[PDB]
Amino acid sequence: YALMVSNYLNWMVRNLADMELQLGAVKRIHGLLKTEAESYEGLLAPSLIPKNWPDQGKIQIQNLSVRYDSSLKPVLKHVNALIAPGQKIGICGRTGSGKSSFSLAFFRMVDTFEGHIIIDGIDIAKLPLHTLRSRLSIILQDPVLFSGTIRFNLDPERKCSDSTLWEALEIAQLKLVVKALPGGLDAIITEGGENFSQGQRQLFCLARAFVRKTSIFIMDEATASIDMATENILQKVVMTAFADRTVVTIAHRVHTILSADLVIVLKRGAILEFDKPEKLLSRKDSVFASFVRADK
Amino acid sequence: RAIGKLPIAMRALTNYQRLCEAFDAQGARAIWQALSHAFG
Amino acid sequence: YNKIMHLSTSNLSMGEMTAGQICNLVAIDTNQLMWFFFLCPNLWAMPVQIIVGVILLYYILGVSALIGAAVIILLAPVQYFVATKLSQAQRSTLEYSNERLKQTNEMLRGIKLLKLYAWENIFRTRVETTRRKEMTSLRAFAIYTSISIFMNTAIPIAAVLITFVGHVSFFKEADFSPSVAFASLSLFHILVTPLFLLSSVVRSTVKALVSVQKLSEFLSSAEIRDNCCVQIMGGYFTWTPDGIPTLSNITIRIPRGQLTMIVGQVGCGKSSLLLAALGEMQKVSGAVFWSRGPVAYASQKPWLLNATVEENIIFESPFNKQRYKMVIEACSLQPDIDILPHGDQTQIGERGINLSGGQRQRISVARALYQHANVVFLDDPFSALDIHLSDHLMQAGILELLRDDKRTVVLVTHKLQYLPHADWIIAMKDGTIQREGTLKDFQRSECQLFEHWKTLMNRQDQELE
Amino acid sequence: PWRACAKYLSSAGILLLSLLVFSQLLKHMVLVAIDYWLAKWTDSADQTVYAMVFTVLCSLGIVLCLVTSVTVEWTGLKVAKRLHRSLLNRIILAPMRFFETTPLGSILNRFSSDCNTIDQHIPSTLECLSRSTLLCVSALAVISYVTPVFLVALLPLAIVCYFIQKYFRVASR
Ligand SMILES: Nc1ncnc2c1ncn2[C@@H]1O[C@H](COP(=O)(O)OP(=O)(O)OP(=O)(O)O)[C@@H](O)[C@H]1O
Ligand SMILES: Nc1ncnc2c1ncn2[C@@H]1O[C@H](COP(=O)(O)OP(=O)(O)O)[C@@H](O)[C@H]1O
Ligand SMILES: [Mg+2]
Ligand SMILES: [Mg+2]
């Protein structure tokens, strides 16, 4: 047993060293295990919330101002906008002026330090967050596709019909490209969408937004990556087919926002104007008028 | 700075040149044959 | 990395290898092969240790040591049984963990889409089922490693039982001194000290064998083989090496020192001409006629090296400070460098600060201006930017800096308002180029597509030239 | 004595932890008992009664070897189940600013490499550590039994073992 402890003293000390050395992985996973919460619960009861609670697009922005985190500056200022029921309203403005954060303010990713938005008489901070983000729809500028198949990229729940997949593909205007694929609704999208184009990646992500059949569409700059002929055909087929729904759109080019009904111009986080674009073009000292004459 | 640079063998070019001279003598059997002739 | 530096980029896009698998191959399988070369002289020194053990057993206690050594030569079929069972469990382990790693990286980039669309429990259930198939393979691995550890410790005291029971019984009565007993017990225990290690050795061998399979699988893939700086004439180009040609018969002519623009629809060949002119597509037929030299490039998706901002402008050029001021005054990062916590020494990227989205496009085209490379290939620089920054990037930058020292630039832009500014324009339709030439040439013949671009700009009163 | 080690033992369970430390101490104790009966039976030279008790405590060594092996795989399997899907259920409920702050490759390197280290590498480290540690202290106890002068000799080698380990560990970290 003198020979035994001379045989195994090295394995005692090196396995103590490897147990501490691989115990650092347990330290790092316990470091990630104690992270913070998004607080997914709701202080409003879901019996009192209706099934079609977002039934009519009556959005009351009431003194809402946001920051991304609690240390930072107010990104949006004291904004107050009455969004009317079935109406198509758009926002344009400068880069970094609050345009994408206005779309994040409806879903409460970005946090509000004052005011509240009101949909349908229901406070959105007084709401369960999964029921909030399930029944409203955002489409974002950067296309994040997933791999797997086209139908799983279209609906990952397995609950939708393939004719509605073809119809949302029809209003995406990608239907001849997916029909000419030899798989063709259950072919393969690869990882990061590198099977297809950048505007096709965006177009698949817009059809992912279209297949959810909601009542409040909100959009970011989603016509930014794509062609102008496809975006003019696209704004025609989205403003015919979703005509009852409230469609909110950040516009990259501001010539497609002339067909909208009311226009917010944001600059430095504030509502510079809240009018019809014909009235905003007829003023001619407006920042919207210098947008539309600086573009063309 | 307190640890140094390498010696010239075990510096990665010259054992990257020990390899593919190892594949110059000729698949995973060729992988194992070049690995055995490179580092036997 | 030498296989990486001549790899076809079609292998990344058509499935077979993803980028997480390629860096995972370095991060795991070279390390597993390294642990096999750490443990390879243990398997080269095992059998002479056990045969000089049994011949010293034949010297010490006689012929009942072979009856005692019957269990140690009986260890080889049970090590073959756990060898084939741990091989099948290690292969199922590696394929389910590769599916779990690819799904977890695919989830974690899409957190911003996934929490907004509220699908995180569905994707987490899919990763949970992949983890369930993994935990099935690892509970198989746990049971087969358990019976190998129990066999590798339980054969020694079975050898002390068969030897020390068979010596005091009447098969022989030669030596019941304590000398042969304690000397043989130390001989069994130094026989036993390989067998504590031997199971970790053979699971490292099977991890080595599948890593050498995936190293040979990664090392077998396909590889990249008059003032007209670019003169691709008549050449068919494909994405898929056995598929239909995505690019058909193209006859392009890029003029030297001169801006040309590439117009078409979505998915029409529009960045595919840039990657065919680079040679990143494999060729069906035809010819490229370069000048190859170094060509400046910024892609549609901008790519970021994780370094400082100044190192992402320069990108192993010389740091001349004056043209660096010229490209940051042309790309207009001068309002956006002061919003960074450092100046240009803010480290950015994946392991750094998260950027805006327009700023990564502006820093990739600010990489594209600073190269002296005389041919500048540009995918869409005004996609993520507004009309103010694309107008300041059109009055400065392109037509101002690079018009002065006469560098060739091509442009790919969905925005058609800068189509006055040209020296040539390539019109495209669906993998074929449509027609080539200038704007006076384009109202001369293709008046339908000229009127198609006239309708979209809303300049019906204005003459387009 | 990190808190991750206490997280490792408390995530395992008091049942499997008690089965591990109890069956490991009884397995090394009946190995101690088999050579002490080898001493008493070689030193006697009632015959084969001292081979019957040798067989019956050797069988306790066999089944105690089996229960130590199945407890070290069941502890490795239960913490490899349990330190996933509490992590994944915590990181999926994380707020968006934490994804904006932290690098993604740090989080994904935990989900790859530290989950693979918590999977495959550590239960082999546990069985080799428990075998080497309880085997060395039981061998130190039995050569404390045969000579009491080795305790007087043993405290210099223990204090130079602690001194060379304290001398090494700040270079090793
Ligand atoms: N990396 C790739 N690998 C394989 N096929 C591709 C790849 N990129 C595009 N394709 C296919 O080739 C066709 C041409 O796409 P291309 O890359 O020309 O798009 P693009 O028009 O340049 O995109 P954008 O409109 O954003 O400029 C697309 O229909 C797409 O399905
Ligand atoms: N993830 C973030 N964290 C902190 N601040 C941000 C973040 N994203 C954007 N900001 C800041 O919020 C402001 C509004 O930008 P944003 O709404 O994203 O773009 P824009 O209004 O230009 O389309 C910007 O000035 C930016 O600095
Ligand atoms: Mg924005
Ligand atoms: Mg493209």
Image: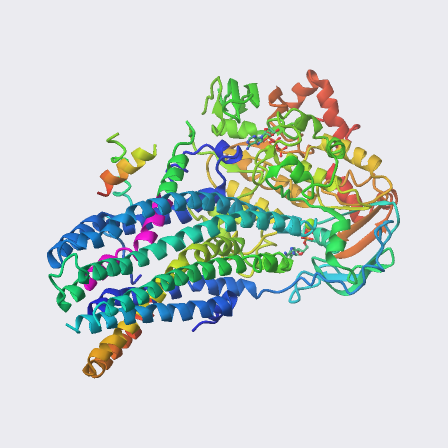
Instruction: Return the x and y of residue C245 as percentages of the image width and height.
Output: 55, 21
The answer to whether residue D41 is above or below residue D125 is below
Report x, y in % for residue A75. 70, 59
Vertical side of A54 occupied by D42: above or below: below
Asked if residue D30 can be seen in this view, the reply is yes
Would you place residue C177 above or below residue A138 in this image?
Answer: below
Front in this rendered view, residue A113 or C377? A113
The image shows residue C444, relative to residue A191, as above or below, that is above
In this picture, residue A209 sits left or right of residue D119: right
Residue at 58% from the left image edge and 64% from the top image edge: A35
Q: Position of residue A86 (x, y in %)?
A: 88, 45
**Within the magenta stretch, is there residue C206?**
yes
What is the magenta range? C185-208
Percent position of residue B15, x then y? 26, 43
The secondary structure that dominates the magenta segment is: helix
Residue at point 48% right, 17% down?
Answer: C286
Considering the image in quadrants, where does the C terminus of chain D appear?
Answer: bottom left
- Would you say residue C158 sits in the magenta stretch? no
